[PDB]
Length: 62
Length: 149
Ligand SMILES: [Ca+2]
Ligand SMILES: [Ca+2]
Image 1: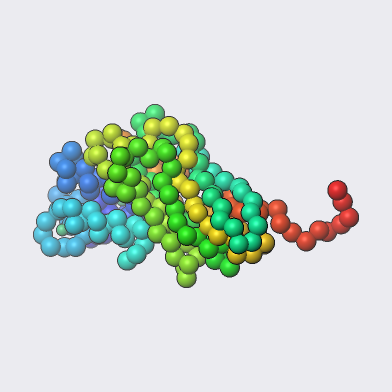
Image 2: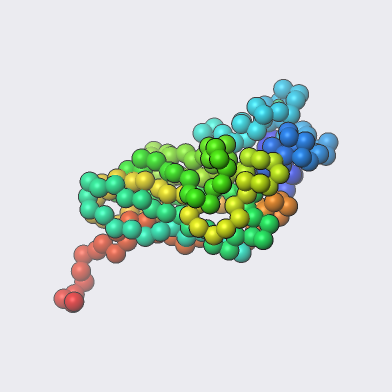
């Protein structure tokens, strides 16, 4: 539902970014609900491109 | 919790100044990430760049640290997210987080102010209590109200 809100706490911030990058490096595992929130470009995969898109959003360029 | 202090500096019109952003009360499990927004007046300050401070330990700082400058929006944005994925590049000590480089455009005070904060988390993703102290350039510049020393 709320794209970018990886941890599902209702706000999009850099803590979601940490969670996203650690999951992409397989340092953590996401819950299924979190996976839907993590796929920020909605292409069906969670990867480095999602990390970069979320970073751009947090830097407010988009 | 964490205290973020914007330094206070002085400088003549036309000169470049550096405004440091200090971190205190760094958590026992470090800072894995932080995002926040400061406000500034582009009539007073032309922000030419923001450099990472020495508490950014990633040997390639741009992997962990990025900023954005918006003169039209009158804001500057900070994004830190330690890039190791293991907590290795987290912030572990108090010190300078960033240095804001600005050319002084007028003698009026050039306040740099806390606008918004997202999250400040440690290596366990525990969000921290955070407070800000505003600062900027020539903070006391004013028309005198009386005759005084
Ligand atoms: Ca969140
Ligand atoms: Ca994706």
